[PDB]
Image (tube, rainbow, N blue to C red):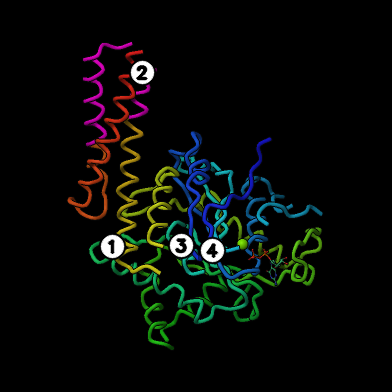
Amino acid sequence: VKKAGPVQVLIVKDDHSFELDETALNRILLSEAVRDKEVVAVSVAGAFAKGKSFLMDFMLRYMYNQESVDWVGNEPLTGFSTTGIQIWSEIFLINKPDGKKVAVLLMDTQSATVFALSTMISSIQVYNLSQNVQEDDLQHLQLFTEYGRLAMEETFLKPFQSLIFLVRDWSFPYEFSYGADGGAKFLEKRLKVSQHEELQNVRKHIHSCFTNISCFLLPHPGLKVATNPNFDGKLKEIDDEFIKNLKILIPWLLSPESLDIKEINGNKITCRGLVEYFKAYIKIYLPHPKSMLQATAEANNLAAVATAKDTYNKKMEEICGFLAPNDLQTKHLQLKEESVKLFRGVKKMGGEEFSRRYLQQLESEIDELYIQYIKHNDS
Ligand SMILES: Nc1nc2c(ncn2[C@@H]2O[C@H](COP(=O)(O)OP(=O)(O)O)[C@@H](O)[C@H]2O)c(=O)[nH]1
Ligand SMILES: [Mg+2]
């Protein structure tokens, strides 16, 4: 009755207006099992019909069986099948080596608005490119560069985490070998300071905006894959050198040691908090660097509101799950001040005056809960 599958959370509509399916986003990210888990947000983005869903379906095979030597698979390819973002409804909980259980969210990003949105949300952004990295391909990164400068004016903390140029159908395998090492060699050459003055500046600045930039060169997958849209054939019908490098690529993106937890201004993000980033970014969607930065600070403060409120809520439920009215008030005022202190201790963006508004929202939401608890205790 219940089965994982792709869920449309962002849709472009026919009037060219973007809409966020908050109900669907909440249903997937606010489940009891994942809401408080730190999240790795994985996105595959790029031009239409360049093999993104095909890649993601192999990413699914690995995620569902990370510990299997045969995870890759005559087994047909299933999973992800215009403009928008689809997310996989199974938020994978993966054991990290440090003892954390992290949430892993996969997003298929199929427009510059959708591309900017997925990059702001992601902590691993796979930029899927066909055959080569073109100047237009780098020009798309320029707004992220300019947002990064404004964000870093007063801190050394970078706004973005991992970016991967995944070059499909690679053409030059002698000088730049298939895989990550040839890709790094190639990317260094392509990024070497130029071209149009705007593209010189993207090259100068891009490494300052991203914690990790890398590049993987993938072979052509063979005629059968290249020619049939719904390629329902054997793994034996896929080029063997493609499969060899695919088996390296996917754990290189997604192994437990590889998963990069989303973080902003030093704060690890939870699935609960990540919803606040979707909601703040959808409102500004191209926007200005200042509008992008203000949306980031707003989500950053609201993620702290959500964390402090949930803390007060679960500790109060543990208390009302009959107490004297003044013992219920005293415990309320104590737990409320603890959540207030929790919120004040978070390193939040925007400045004290900016954050005062969100502290007052926190206090109001906490008082809303308290009145519910009194009614539950009067009963
Ligand atoms: N040439 C080429 N085609 C591919 C590759 N990977 C998948 N395809 C084929 O590209 C077509 C479109 O793939 P799809 O995953 O739907 O592209 P998407 O729109 O980016 O999600 C299908 O026929 C795939 O079988 C690749 O590495 N190179
Ligand atoms: Mg797609």
Residue at mark 3 to residue at mark 1: CA–CA distance: 20 Å
Between disc 4 and disc 2, the foreground one is: 2
**Which numbered tag is attached to residue 376?**
2
Between disc 4 and disc 3, the foreground one is: 3
Taking the spot 30% from the left edge, 55% from the top edge, the residue there is: 297
**Which numbered tag is attached to residue 126?**
4
Q: Earlier in the sequence, mark 3 or mark 1?
A: 3
Measured from the top left, where is residue 327 in percent x and y?
A: 23, 15
Disc 3, ligand 2: is the CB inside 8 Å? no
Q: Nearer the viewer, residue 99 or 35?
A: 35
Residue at mark 4 to residue at mark 3: CA–CA distance: 9 Å
Relative to 332, residue 131 above or below = below
Which image quadrant: the C terminus?
top left
Residue at mark 3 to residue at mark 2: CA–CA distance: 43 Å
Q: Is residue 106 visible from the viewing direction of this image?
A: yes
Q: Earlier in the sequence, mark 1 or mark 2?
A: 1
Helix, strand or loop for disc 1: loop
Between disc 3 and disc 1, the foreground one is: 3
Relative to 135, residue 97 above or below = above
- Asked if residue 228 lies left or right of residue 198, the reply is right
